[PDB]
């Protein structure tokens, strides 16, 4: 596993997240279940706790956008770039963006939202990409859930 320069991590163990908008190809309920499961993957192995808020600014703002969407990481339409997230810190730190031009699903037909979200949240928590091919933080999409050992070691190094 790998961490970001200066080992970025959250100072508090009680973090908030907010789903700003939704993708059209999935019902609001399935999008919410996807993220709920994504956060659980990480809360189960760390002393971290996540609370979903609906108004205001949360520690982790989740949004869907297309092409140019407000930052220095524009999307590229169907396929290619799927999503990106920012490491722990103020402002957009911790935020996760998902390409709305993708066909997100709860199954395995298109790009599974849960698995991508789980990967992105790893970044939101302080983990950079891993060199271990079987790690969730490996930079390649492959959907077949139990968090691989490399990821557990990495996240527990930061918050354990
Ligand atoms: O790493 C990225 C972006 C890309 S990605 O958009 O293609 C991408 C995002 C999340 C992914 O998640 C998973 C990783 C591993 C497994 Cl097993 C499942 C999902 C995969 C690719 C594109 C640029 O180069 C690295 C990969 N940020 O998370
Ligand atoms: Ca894309
Ligand atoms: Ca933040
Ligand atoms: Zn973005
Ligand atoms: Zn990544």
Image: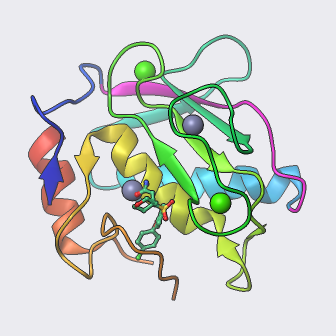
Residue sitting at x 82%, y 51%: 23
Residue sitting at x 27%, y 82%: 134
Q: What number of labels is visible? A: 0
Asked whether, in this view, residue 129 is left or right of residue 65, the answer is left
Residue 18 in the magenta stretch? The answer is yes
Asked whether, in this view, residue 15 is left or right of residue 87, the answer is right
Q: Position of residue 66 (x, y in %)?
A: 74, 44
Residue 146 in the magenta stretch? The answer is no
Asked whether, in this view, residue 132 is left or right of residue 134, the answer is left
Q: Is residue 43 visible?
A: no
Residue sitting at x 67%, y 84%: 108
Report the magenta residues as a range: 13-25
Q: Nearer the viewer, residue 121 or 82?
A: 82
Residue sitting at x 35%, y 45%: 123
Asked whether, in this view, residue 56 is left or right of residue 80, the answer is right
Q: Position of residue 95 (x, y in %)?
A: 50, 32
Q: Position of residue 22 (x, y in %)?
A: 81, 44
Q: Is residue 92 above or below residue 57?
A: below
Q: Is residue 149 visible?
A: yes
Q: Position of residue 154 (x, y in %)?
A: 15, 55
Q: Is residue 64 above or below residue 20?
A: below
Quadrant into which the C terminus falls? top left
């Amino acid at each position: 596993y790998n961490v970001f320069p200066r080992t970025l991590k959250w100072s508090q163990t009680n973090l908030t997240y907010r789903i700003v908008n939704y993708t059209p190809d999935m019902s609001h309920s399935e999008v919410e279940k996807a993220f709920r499961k994504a956060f659980k993957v990480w809360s189960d192995v760390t002393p971290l706790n996540f609370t979903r808020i609906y108004d205001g600014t949360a520690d982790i703002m989740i949004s869907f956008g297309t092409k140019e969407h407000g930052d220095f990481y524009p999307f590229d339409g169907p396929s290619g770039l799927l999503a990106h997230a920012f490491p722990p810190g103020p402002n957009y730190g911790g935020d996760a963006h998902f390409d709305d031009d993708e066909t997100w699903t709860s199954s395995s037909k298109g790009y599974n939202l849960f698995i991508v979200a789980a990967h992105e949240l790893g970044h939101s928590l302080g983990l950079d990409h891993s060199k271990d091919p079987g790690a969730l933080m490996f930079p390649i999409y492959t959907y077949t859930f139990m968090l691989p050992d490399d990821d557990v070691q990495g996240i527990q190094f930061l918050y354990g």
